[PDB]
Amino acid sequence: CPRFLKVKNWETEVVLTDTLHLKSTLETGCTEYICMGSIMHPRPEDVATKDQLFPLAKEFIDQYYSSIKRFGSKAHMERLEEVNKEIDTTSTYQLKDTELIYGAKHAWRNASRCVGRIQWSKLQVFDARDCTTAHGMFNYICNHVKYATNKGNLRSAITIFPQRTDGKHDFRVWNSQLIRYAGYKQPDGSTLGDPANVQFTEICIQQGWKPPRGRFDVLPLLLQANGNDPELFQIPPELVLEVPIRHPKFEWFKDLGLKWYGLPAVSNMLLEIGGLEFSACPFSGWYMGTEIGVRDYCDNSRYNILEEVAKKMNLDMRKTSSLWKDQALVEINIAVLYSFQSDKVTIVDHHSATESFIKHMENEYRCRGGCPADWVWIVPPMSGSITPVFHQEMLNYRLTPSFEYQPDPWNTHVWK
Amino acid sequence: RFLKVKNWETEVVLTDTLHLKSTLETGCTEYICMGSIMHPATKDQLFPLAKEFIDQYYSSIKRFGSKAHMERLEEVNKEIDTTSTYQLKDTELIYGAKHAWRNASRCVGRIQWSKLQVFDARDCTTAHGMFNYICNHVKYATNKGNLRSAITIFPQRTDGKHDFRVWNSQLIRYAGYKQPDGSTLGDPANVQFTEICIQQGWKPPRGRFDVLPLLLQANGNDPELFQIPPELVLEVPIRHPKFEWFKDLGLKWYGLPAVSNMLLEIGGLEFSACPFSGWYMGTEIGVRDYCDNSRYNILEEVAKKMNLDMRKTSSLWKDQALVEINIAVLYSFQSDKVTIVDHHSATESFIKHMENEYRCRGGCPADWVWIVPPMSGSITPVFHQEMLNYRLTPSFEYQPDPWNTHVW
Ligand code: HEM
Ligand code: HEM
Ligand SMILES: CNCCN(C)c1cncc(CCc2cc(C)cc(N)n2)c1
Ligand SMILES: CNCCN(C)c1cncc(CCc2cc(C)cc(N)n2)c1
Ligand SMILES: C[C@H](O)[C@H](O)[C@H]1CNc2nc(N)[nH]c(=O)c2N1
Ligand SMILES: C[C@H](O)[C@H](O)[C@H]1CNc2nc(N)[nH]c(=O)c2N1
Ligand SMILES: [Cl-]
Ligand SMILES: [Cl-]
Ligand SMILES: [Zn+2]
């Protein structure tokens, strides 16, 4: 592979030079003959062997002591020797708190699909590696939610549960996000709530959950500690900050009865650091408007409200070339930003977030020699070309530490 | 491997086998994806390429290994032997042209691929001849508003020293003028080319929408200027169906979108002059030409007339202004009976086309970055459609701008 790769911004003519790609550790899925850049997702109870683990650990440890300007130091070599000893005797090792914090911040930093990474170094890391039970997990998660929510003044946070051992003792949050609304399939084929969540909702209901059967019912947490069967907990409602959607102009918009939750928090991903696998590592930030206004509300397979809004806007909905869909999409997204700003809950519009990302990316090319980015994910789902990211060439590659996808636990769990 | 692509909205899964046919590079490797990068012979090199292309043509007409097939392979060999090149049969030219379109991964309009009027211009020898051939192209494809897809193919490359090139990147473009005060009149994107035209004798009216002349190079010679007769150039004044003040913005655009800077490769042959044209998707004009910062850049003005709050970005004034501009463009072309497709219709058709291609052909190469429209992405079906990108031949490829390679 070539040492220097160049990306261009076609709006500004600015050209950046990437050398960081050379540190690429994993596979994109693409080859020279095919590109899989728009594929969403391109192993049994299986864990890293001693020989696989040594080099991955050294790689990470080197990188860490390089970052604190102590590469090749006595404390660097001693840490190498201590880790290598731990792998030899125990087939694994434990990260120091300093290294855990570095690794988490870097996994976010390396997350090519995140437009919010300007904030990567401000991340509160809760070390939950002493957790042993589902109730314990519940406690840690509640604390995360409250801290991150901060009464509306959101703060990004991640809570890391114990790493994987033999693969039969995994900690998992079964929820894909900490806060989601339930979906219920009706006998008639209609759906109530969020149609996307019918499967998970069914699982909950089976585990003992009593469903309110509403449009915006917060799901319980389904928590798995040390490989045991998962257990249900209801998040205390006072910890779940919500925002009712209203529009600065349309008085009738509040009559749609829409609202959304303040905190975006992903909990189905796997954090890999130095070859160690943290299968439960919920992390949370704050919303970009379009996540709600466009995808949650206007995806056909989600809440699908374009039609209903278009009707209350009295738009001609017979031709598509009237662009009634597009007009209603903008208004919805205006109401979302306005409802969040009015309740003083943190939210960033897609224009501000993308400009910030460009400034971030440029800084990263300057200080780091690169910034992996997934254009398909970074460009917002509305108004794409009037945001600066659309015109920015990006290179995508996988650096470690990283957040990775993992199988859904209900497909793999062995029931006790 | 066989590869699966999934649509996340319909949960439809298609199986791609066609990608196994490709050979040219994508730019990506196992470790680095360049999916968002815009730009990533000899007797011995020529024949296998020739061979393959002939092979797939006789395969496409259900006569693989026939007597016609054999003599053709023999013919091409003897001709590459003695002349260092070969000339395509008429039927091969048309097949190659339609398939270059069919294989164009960045094109959302490909459901139309087999309906393409092919103009064989391989007997052209001078710039005047090229102009005649291009005028006929424009007129046929314009067709008084009822646009029809067309391509005009000039002589193939020989030694790279006697190339045919249309120097305009598109057959119809507006000029761009660099003002003293540092502002830019017209289309800023073409400011350079415009100046090249002036430097060669073009007399600029210096307005906001002056149609550039054609600049045409035949057989490696210095290019020559020609003005397309105005009656061949169909233009549409843009107005809004509700905002009667919109016509006062004074905007117009041309009806014929016609790419002329690309290279058409068939059977190892290179057609460096092959202007091709179709009809517009509304966003091309409404979003890119008008609203790109480096283009006509009209958002702010329109936002003024719409009386929007422009102090903070979170009012989405930019987004609002954008939708109305695109409504106007669709409304104008439609009212003037000029062919145009909206991004909802064009994207639906493309998904349908993908289905067809997987069914009959075993795949459909597609560039998600280019196919998804530049506005309202996720309320179109292609946003949710996984796509595999790969390079099939015959194809349209990029080439150097001739003004960086030509000796006068
Ligand atoms: C602080 C404000 C943040 C903003 C504005 C932000 C923005 C976004 C957005 C808009 C997406 C696309 C989400 C989707 O379409 O589902 C995304 C994805 C992602 N973000 Fe960020 N994010 C933030 C915080 C964080 C934090 C704190 C982390 C990790 C420590 C993180 C890591 C990721 C990852 C791994 C993805 C990929 C998700 C997936 O593959 O499903 N983000 N981000
Ligand atoms: C008939 C209706 C057609 C429609 C609606 C259509 C639509 C589009 C659009 C919207 C683009 C993106 C253009 C841009 O953003 O610059 C595009 C690109 C492209 N089209 Fe089509 N097109 C049509 C016909 C054709 C024809 C007739 C050909 C060739 C025979 C063709 C070949 C291509 C190629 C090679 C590109 C890539 C352009 C580039 O790389 O700059 N298209 N098309
Ligand atoms: C379109 N993506 C599907 C995921 N999805 C429906 C979803 C549901 N609920 C919450 C999120 C949040 C995604 C996210 C995560 C983080 C850390 C920040 C942020 N702004 N968004 C996503
Ligand atoms: C993003 N576009 C850059 C090129 N550009 C400004 C441009 C100028 N003039 C015309 C076109 C047309 C592109 C095109 C080509 C074809 C065959 C069909 C179509 N609908 N659009 C593009
Ligand atoms: C097929 C395509 O990869 C898929 O629809 C992607 C497109 N880009 C996206 N971008 C973001 N931010 N989130 C998404 O879920 C998706 N979905
Ligand atoms: C950087 C990026 O590749 C570039 O802006 C692309 C994105 N997608 C596009 N899509 C279309 N149709 N046309 C374009 O010019 C572009 N530009
Ligand atoms: Cl932000
Ligand atoms: Cl079409
Ligand atoms: Zn790729």
Image (spheres, coloured by chain):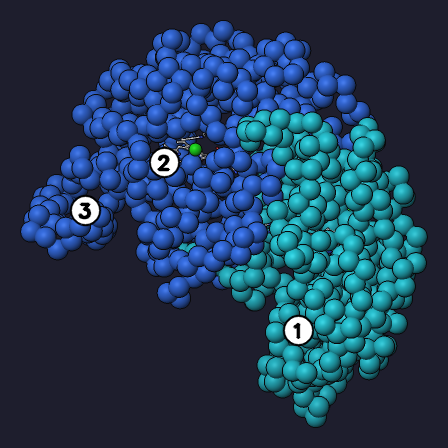
Chain colours: A blue, B cyan
Residue B158 at x, y percent in the picture = 69, 83
Q: Nearer the viewer, residue B223 or A409?
A: B223
The residue type indicated by label 2 comes to: Gln
| Residue B151 in view of the camera | yes
| Image quarter of residue B377 | top right
Give yes or no for contact between labels 2 and 3 (Cβ–Cβ under 8 Å): no
**Quadrant where the image shows the C terminus of chain B:** bottom right
The residue type indicated by label 1 comes to: Pro
Quickly name the residue at label 3.
Answer: A68
| Residue B120 in view of the camera | no
Residue found at the far front of this picture: B181
Quickly name the residue at label 2.
Answer: A119
Identify the secondary structure beneath mark 1: helix
Residue A406 at x, y percent in the picture = 38, 37
Tally the marks. 3
Chain of the residue on which disc 3 is drawn = A
Quickly name the residue at label 1.
Answer: B402
Badges 1 and 3, same chain:
no
Residue A327 at x, y percent in the picture = 70, 28
Chain of the residue on which disc 1 is drawn = B
Q: Residues within 10 Å of mark 1 (few under 14, many from 20)?
A: some
Tell whether B249 sits left or right of A24: right
What residue appears at the point 88 percent right and 39 percent down from the top-left corner?
A: B335
What residue appears at the point 18 percent right and 37 percent down from the top-left corner?
A: A98
Chain of the residue on which disc 2 is drawn = A
How far apart are labels 2 and 1 at the CA level? Answer: 45 Å
Report whether the residue tagged 2 is closer than 8 Å to ligand 1: yes
